[PDB]
Image (cartoon, rainbow, N blue to C red):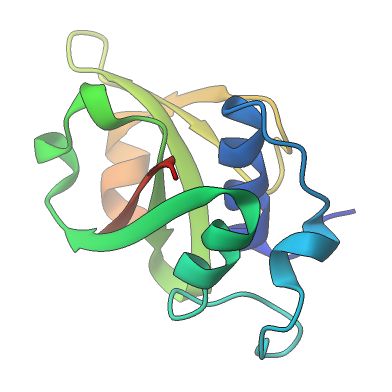
Length: 125
């Protein structure tokens, strides 16, 4: 059972890129907090995966579909992958710690209420 939301989100993106990385490799040599990744460590974890991750600020509806999947920082130390947003149906597709590796649909309103305004742009090295 995965408990680290940022690690779950990073593993999903690594896998989306066909990059095989144990959760172990991704945290190797990093100083975790209460056993978990934080936004401060995530660029170095991404490097260990063969990715580049960079934190940015944007309102949710300003994030381009073109850069997805992105990792959203959510209130309370949580995170998810943003896979897509449909503005017609007002639904977002996200991958959460509870959904594991499976993207799920949620109401856009719900994501807006938890989103902090900060996200990671993730791409291959």
